[PDB]
Amino acid sequence: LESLSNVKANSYSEWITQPNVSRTIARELKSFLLEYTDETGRSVYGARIRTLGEMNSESLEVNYRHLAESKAILALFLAKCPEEMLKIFDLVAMEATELHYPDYARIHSEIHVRISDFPTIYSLRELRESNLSSLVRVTGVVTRRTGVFPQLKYVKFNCLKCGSILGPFFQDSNEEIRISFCTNCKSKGPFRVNGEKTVYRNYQRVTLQEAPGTVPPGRLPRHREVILLADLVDVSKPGEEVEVTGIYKNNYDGNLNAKNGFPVFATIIEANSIKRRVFSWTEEEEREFRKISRDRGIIDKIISSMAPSIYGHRDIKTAVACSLFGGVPKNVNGKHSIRGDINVLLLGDPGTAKSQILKYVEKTAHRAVFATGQGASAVGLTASVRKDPITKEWTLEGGALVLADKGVCLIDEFDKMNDQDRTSIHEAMEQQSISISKAGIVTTLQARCSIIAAANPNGGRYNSTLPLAQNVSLTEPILSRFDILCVVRDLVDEEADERLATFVVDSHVRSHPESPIPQELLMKYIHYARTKIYPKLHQMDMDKVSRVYADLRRESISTGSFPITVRHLESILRIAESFAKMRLSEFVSSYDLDRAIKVVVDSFVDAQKVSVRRQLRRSFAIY
Amino acid sequence: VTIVGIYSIYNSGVAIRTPYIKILGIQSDVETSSIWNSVTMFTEEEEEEFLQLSRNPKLYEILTNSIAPSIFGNEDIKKAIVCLLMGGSKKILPDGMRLRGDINVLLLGDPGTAKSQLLKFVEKVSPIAVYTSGKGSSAAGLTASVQRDPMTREFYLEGGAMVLADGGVVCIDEFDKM
Amino acid sequence: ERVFQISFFNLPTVHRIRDIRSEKIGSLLSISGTVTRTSEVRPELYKASFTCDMCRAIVDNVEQSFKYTEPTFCPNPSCENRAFWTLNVTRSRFLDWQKVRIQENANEIPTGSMPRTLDVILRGDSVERAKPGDRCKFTGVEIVVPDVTQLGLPGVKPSSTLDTRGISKTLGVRDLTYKISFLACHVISIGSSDEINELKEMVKDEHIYDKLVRSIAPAVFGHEAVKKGILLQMLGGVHKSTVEGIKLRGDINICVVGDPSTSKSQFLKYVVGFAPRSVYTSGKASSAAGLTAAVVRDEEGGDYTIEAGALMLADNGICCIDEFDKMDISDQVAIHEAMEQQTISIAKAGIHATLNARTSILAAANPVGGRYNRKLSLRGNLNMTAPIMSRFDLFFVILDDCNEKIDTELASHIVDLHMKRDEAIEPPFSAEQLRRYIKYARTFKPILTKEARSYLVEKYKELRKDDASSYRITVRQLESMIRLSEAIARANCVDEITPSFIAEAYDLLRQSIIRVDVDD
Amino acid sequence: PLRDLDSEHVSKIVRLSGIIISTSVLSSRATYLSIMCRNCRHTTSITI
Ligand SMILES: Nc1ncnc2c1ncn2[C@@H]1O[C@H](COP(=O)(O)OP(=O)(O)OP(=O)(O)O)[C@@H](O)[C@H]1O
Ligand SMILES: Nc1ncnc2c1ncn2[C@@H]1O[C@H](COP(=O)(O)OP(=O)(O)O)[C@@H](O)[C@H]1O
Ligand SMILES: [Mg+2]
Ligand SMILES: [Mg+2]
Ligand SMILES: [Zn+2]
Ligand SMILES: [Zn+2]
Ligand SMILES: [Zn+2]
């Protein structure tokens, strides 16, 4: 035959499987792979198989537009009965790889085929009984996920009469296969599969749910089950919208038809291709990082890139950057631990863009976890032992503090926590580790994380006439583990109102239908800086630091304020380390020390009562 | 732990099997040293070394200097900690009464005097030690707790730092809140 | 090959679910009810094909008739097979199949009794036509299906056994318990034309706003501000999306505060009786699953399904909540989750899902102490929590003032209503007219103007300066003012917000804040 | 990693790290059995 397939003998499935037409279509698919070329004249598929061989891959992606344009008839019969043509084109791809590469079967016995660019897009609610055993393309969100399981591929059997091991028999992924004849014995007795001589592949089940935005008002989202085989497993984790191309078919096995009631069937989708509807770098990016670092005034370059969707609050943003870069931990002889994570506290009046700051930090950090003292959240703060609903096994789970080891833990509504949450937070901050004694398990988990918190004052309004300790429900042991306290007051002013109101109204009008470093580069900059920079100190700044500390101590004791203690010196050193890290330098300059001094002194002064505050403003005017 | 074994399957989709591991070796990283897993045998070299160290005329000074050399001052506190770690001598009497031999110490002070780092060092340096606060820890009580077994539905000691640290030292922070 | 379906409709009479009798089994009638649940559409075995075993003969197009049926004899004398067959799932046909659960109408439930439910089966092209929370009129056949649950009931239950007289010699007994179901063929919901002329005439009025305000809750005396809130709650703002993924709300929420001796509940009753998709619920007669949603995993034929709650119903509508001050903490958190993100996350029985909850909330709250202490502020007189309290963009506190003319006028109105009944209402517009107007006007999406931005900024400055009362002012009130202004512009059927509407919105917002009285 | 185990490792030797969360009670299995026939009293043995 030669492009005479437009003649129809009987139903499409029967036609496609005849040996002669099978050979015809196989040869024509091989010619499609070997000959297809675009206008540029480059061998798109040639390069595809070349890179497949170079990378030692297992699958080739194919475009439906090219195949349609070239061989409309083959494209149509593919859309109708793809089950057989998957096998046919798998064999074609195997022979193509053999032609390009020698003895590829030595490593991989199969090359899978992935289709792409299918013209029609469906929703999970549109599938009906005219789509069964056909090719579909849908989209939705991932809601659950099973583990990876092994499935039989090349089964070998044991004869119980003679110990012969019958040779491999292919498993088709349709129904379990059996054998009945032993060649040596000429027998038919019992058989058992050989576990140690069988080859398996990967199996995974995924449940897809529609995107809530697309559901027309008044109805509810639908869902389906998806099957992922081989190297499609562990590609789409829960919580991401994806596009899946597969074959829509029933559970023809079912359970049995003796069941009472109407004879109805369940259906699944066998995925052929999956796609999604980073913090790594390279030398190309490393050179640009170093170039940007060398420029003067890089700290203020970075600070202006924090939370672009908020106006003002420069102190908040510099503190956020400092806690987002971090210092260097230390340990002397392995018997005296010093922490390197900088904690900040946001204490402001209602309507001051605190939750937005936390959301930005969550969206910009490499490992950020969101919790709260009130409301629904994906995780709590305490460790516990709970059943797994789907696997039905006991599991050990830590809180957001354990989960964010070497990261940042964000807590919203810090003033509304209960006793258990307070105890967990206190232990994590004091010891950087969480204990547990539950259900026969005694252990300790690491809790070395950075904390950014937001709260409200008593009564919802700040009383500037009293010290900070009497404006919040928190206690001294917890409040003293922070080193950057930020106080936001909604004082009424005219120019500020103009600026904020114009910002807000412009924002809204832009979003009606009808200097700063780029963020995508900033993420990689932060990751690289944390990964590769460990600044040190020079003993020549000891005199300056000691003199400043003595001045602060003397003034604090004279004015009868909250005591200045060595914790502030350690915070100053940590912030200086972070500022040095911001520049990619290996040493801490005097300018970083000055910036840290300003930050800590301003934080300390801003948290006192009005009289003490104004007295301390004059004394420390140098900074 | 670190485990070496064989990745295998068994029969409990269409052709699915359940994986599991056949253990060939176990390597433990040393966890939760308690009174039930102590070692009461000493090598002869260690014994001779310790006897030699005992005779040092300046042993008390060296031991005092060893406790947290990274903190300044508080010589009396450190000597108290030496006496605490060593412990007294217990006496059992013919009538049944017990005269304890352990030592209790309290630390009143202002914020930022390095009295939590001393507790942390004592925790890190004692053979058996639990460091906790009043109200216990996250998902870990401060005193003995009795719970019913999830499957057999019967009593056992669920936990409690006070009994877990039997034969050791318990470090309590924020003693005024409980 | 083609499957043909007939569709009867417009029967002379309609039956209630409470008046179905086993006499009309197998006949065509019409019923009505409210839909409670719907399942997914699944293939249904219609004409099966089998392969004989003793011989390789093939049998095609075997009818099922409501149950899984097998061929009764080999079609050829070459084989004498019977009862030994295999099913071919590769050359058979299927039809779409759905199951729907309906409930009695509220006004049809007799005295002292709980409502009934009835299963309804849909086929073919009728599937996916009903919707939960809607009232539909069905037409089809009344049928019977097995009921294994009827064992244990009192009485004698028919049994069947094979007659053994006339059989040469030298156990299959069956039970005949059934229940009544309904297989329907036509379903229609029950709630342009010449009326475009009427619509154009009425929009071309000049004082249309005053009539629109007066026609809301005509049976309640006074309280114009609450009416102007209920209006502008039916008509809402526009939902906006930022480039970075920040979504801006378009819904307006209201809370009416008063003691049990006031008439705040009548507003909620009017809204639920009038608004298209509205649900009424009480603070203490509700539950967490009653709100939000539940999961019913015992789907007798296959996988699970979800059953909508109160918030799920009235999506893109209005939810009324009386006795709002008796909600617990968990339900308050659920309402706050709905208000913050227009979604409801359901996690039960190892099943996760997400559900839209884009709703506007109309709440009525009592003062904490029974009487509104005017010496305290709004926060000190309520029991709510700060998160939910900060999302209510209007607080209407209604109080009682003694005055001769007011009292006599109110008494005259009430006596008129009792004596005259329907006669003494005379509103400018009727409910159908308001519904048509609101349906038309909800599709305009007004926009701001260059002149309006600075005027709005100056109004916000004025309001902030004057604030420096019931509660302080923040930017949240600026967003609320924008929302209200655009809602008013929609209400006036204009494509651009003008400073007049901005002034109207500002005055409405300002008048709703009351002052705290102090001694001396 | 525990999440990196897959089909290619079946029946091979692996090295894994993690935390123990549950140990069971001791069971009993046979290593040598002596058996007898209840009809003719023929006896034999089995080794595991
Ligand atoms: N300075 C500001 N600049 C821009 N938008 C702001 C600013 N302050 C508040 N907003 C906006 O006003 C609203 C305030 O809500 P948000 O949750 O951010 O406040 P918050 O300070 O966390 O208050 P709370 O949680 O106590 O209600 C949000 O829309 C926020 O975007
Ligand atoms: N006398 C001291 N000598 C050395 N370091 C000190 C001293 N006092 C405080 N510090 C520093 O303060 C930290 C301990 O503070 P902290 O344990 O919070 O004290 P407290 O428990 O009394 O509040 C240590 O990291 C240490 O570097
Ligand atoms: Mg907030
Ligand atoms: Mg301390
Ligand atoms: Zn054999
Ligand atoms: Zn036959
Ligand atoms: Zn025998």
Image (cartoon, rainbow, N blue to C red):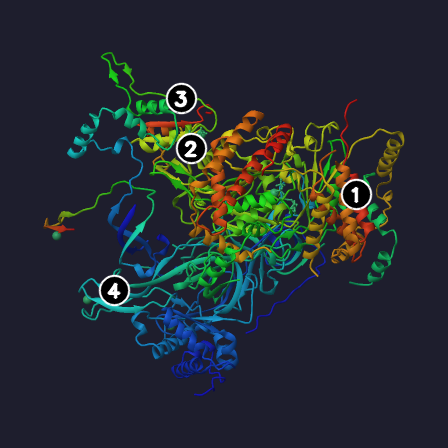
Name the mark nearer the viewer: 2 or 1: 2
Question: Where does label 1 land, which residue?
Answer: C508
Residue at the image point whose x is 45% and y is 79% from the top = A43
Q: Is residue D40 above or below residue C193?
A: above
Q: Which mark is residue A157?
A: 4
Question: Where B39 falls versus C458 (above or below)?
Answer: above
| Residue C310 appears in the rendering | no
Percent of width and height locating residue B27: 26, 45
Q: Quadrant of the N terminus of chain A?
A: bottom left
Task: Mark 1: give few (<14), some (14-19) or many (20+) Cα within 10 Å.
Answer: some
Give the quarter of the image for residue C420: top right
Read off the chain for label 3: B
Disc 3 or 2, which lies upstream in sequence?
3
Q: Position of residue A228 (x, y in %)?
A: 43, 62
Q: Amino acid at mark 3?
A: Leu
Query: Considering depth in this image, is B105 or C237 the residue closer to the camera?
Result: B105
Do the residues at discs 4 and 1 belong to one chain? no
The residue singled out by tag 3 in the image is: B106
* Pair 3/2: label in front: 3
Please identify the quadrant where the C terminus of chain A is shown.
top right
